[PDB]
Image (cartoon, rainbow over all chains, first blue to last red):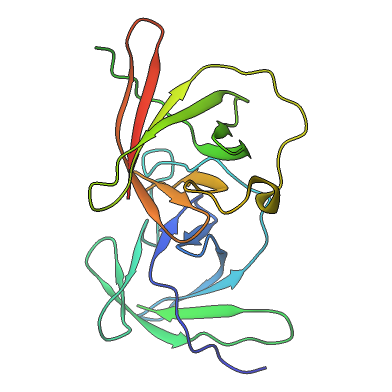
Length: 101
Length: 101
């Protein structure tokens, strides 16, 4: 039930639905709470999915196509916004990431 | 001579020096250019094949077990490496692609 040190470097968007990193590790956004700053819980999920799909065939989105880890552990949105890392925890063979833009 | 735009989304290692894609197409590495990093010539031409090889089976390769195409522009190797597919073409029904680290 503890947090995860090592953080992914990049979170490409695969599907609307699905993000992939450099460890070929699928992450899915499952909730997007909002009040000023929204927050996305990307749960690591198995796949059993494919076909790297385009922005074009994506496309209107609340979340960036890309997510780039910066020197200070902030994630930067493909559209120049910055997202704080809220946690990279794990709860019973369940590994989630919650980003707060 | 013939720039082709839809390149394989997934290179699988069938054996040593034999890859396949989603299409069950044959891709053949003939040259690797150790310039300072890797340059890999891949060329299509189907070869009759049965039981694929195991990674152990194909032994510690020059090449990877699998390349998988990311939305970014590039193929991720089974090793967190990325490869610049610098060209995809055909010279008289002759498919060629170049992959570099």
